[PDB]
Image (cartoon, rainbow, N blue to C red; front, side, top):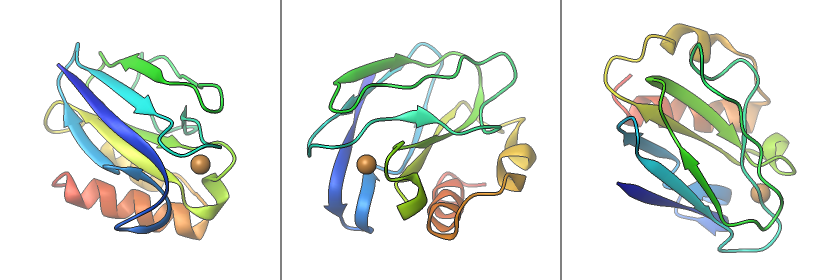
Length: 124
Ligand SMILES: [Cu+2]
């Protein structure tokens, strides 16, 4: 199945957001990151993807379809707006084995609050 994630200048959780900011998918599902507003992209965050998973980084304003395979939690960011809090989490499967590594990684304040909220929204 395919899921859109919208790259937004603002949304219900405020300024510079992925919507949804948390999403649980199955292996083989796709997430299509939509450049709903101009100036955004998507990139995996250092240290925040499962063992054996490929990192990825899209171009700004690119409609970017990612296939997820390896189970676990994936921290994602918008490259230009990471420091301003533009982040999300995609979780593949239940009971993510890399949860503590993901929770432990240091991020700027705004980003960390939204990562933590997304992990909590996913039941972790
Ligand atoms: Cu952005």
